[PDB]
Length: 81
Length: 67
Image (cartoon, rainbow over all chains, first blue to last red; front, side):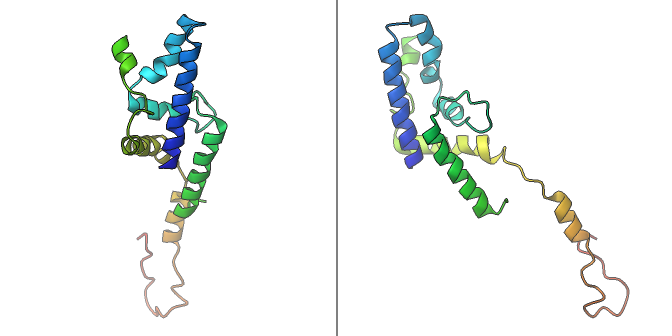
């Protein structure tokens, strides 16, 4: 409930920055906003890709840490390690 | 291209729909990919003859749980 709320707020902020920065590089804006032009399921998939160190996702460290902590708590609840 | 532009990013979507999408994406991206090795311990614990002489057998060796 709150993880998605903060993720949505950040995606609004990044889109605002993209729109404000569109006027300096139009060619960049294409692949820069392909993320916002991607389907919502693909958006979820690409923003939830900070597992491992591939790090192509635009998710910031502060939002990443909350999910990395909740995943550890869930794994402990499941008794995995 | 304006048709792709107008299509709503996640921040326009209602909270519950985005939550459902996040649940699905989290499932595939994290829950499926997470792996732990337990077979070598499970098949060992099952194969262990459990205290058959300690508890009252007084007969042929009872089949182990794996058996």
